Length: 75
Image 1 (cartoon, rainbow, N blue to C red):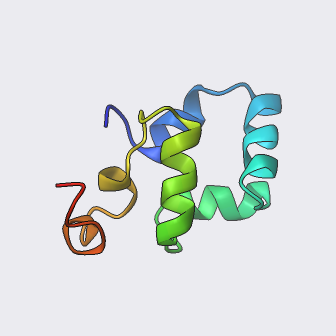
Image 2: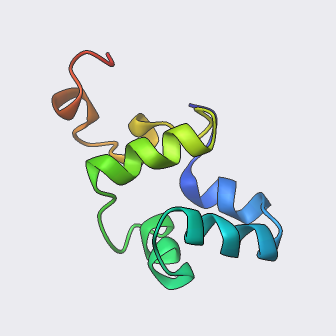
């Protein structure tokens, strides 16, 4: 990918980021905790974020320490 989840959210307008949290089925607080590394991004939600950002925030940035194991085919 090109950027981290935190970097991508930083770039959205506040209104857009509230809509992005809504689209992901999470609260803006939970999205923030995900972007700040305070809680895990589930494998499915990583796929959701990857597809929503057209690959800009990829599963490798969202599960940096075990993406090679969860998706051996992606590598």
